[PDB]
């Protein structure tokens, strides 16, 4: 009973069962278009972390901005309606956050 009868395909599938995924690209002075198919309901704190990981710096280093507005990290990208933007940039956290 303890051993499963078969391994499921849930971790193995990649299409999220024909579900939606984010297409937003964050492109700072790093000049790279690295982005992943995560769901649109995550908070920007995790993206802040993942971008700082592409530079090898802690998450307190950078904040995102687009249309002139730097944004607060507890938003989700669907709150801001930005889930497929061609470019959002980063700028340094001048005094941290």
Image (cartoon, grey):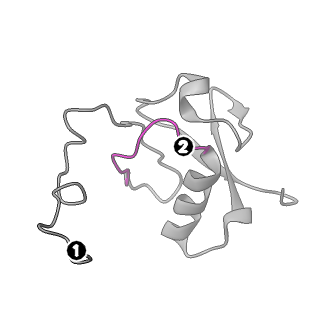
Q: Is residue 88 magenta?
A: no
User: How far across and down, in percent of the image, does residue 79 sit?
Assistant: 61, 25
Q: Quadrant of the C terminus?
A: bottom right
Q: Is residue 42 magenta?
A: yes
- Report the residue at 52% width, 61% height from top: 50
Q: Secondary structure at mark 1?
A: loop
Label 1 Cα crowd, 10 Å radius (few <14 / some 14-19 / many 20+): few
Highlighted range, magenta: 34-43
Q: Is residue 8 left or right of residue 41?
A: left
- Report the residue at 61% width, 44% height from top: 43
User: How far across and down, in percent of the image, does residue 44 sit?
Assistant: 61, 45
Q: Quadrant of residue 25?
A: top left
Q: Quadrant of residue 57?
A: bottom right
Label 2 Cα crowd, 10 Å radius (few <14 / some 14-19 / many 20+): some
Tag shown at residue 42: 2
**In this orientation, which residue lies closer to the viewer: 91 or 5?**
5
Q: Is residue 41 left or right of residue 44?
A: left
């Amino acid at each position: 009973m303890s051993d499963q009868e078969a391994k499921p395909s849930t971790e193995d599938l990649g299409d999220k069962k024909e579900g939606e995924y984010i297409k937003l690209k964050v492109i700072g002075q790093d000049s790279s278009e690295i982005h992943f198919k995560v769901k649109m309901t995550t908070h920007l704190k995790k993206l802040k972390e993942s971008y700082c990981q592409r530079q090898g710096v802690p998450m307190n280093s950078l904040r995102f901005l687009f249309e002139g507005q730097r944004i607060a990290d507890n938003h989700t990208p669907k709150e801001l309606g930005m889930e497929e933007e061609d470019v959002i940039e980063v700028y340094q956290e001048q005094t941290g956050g």
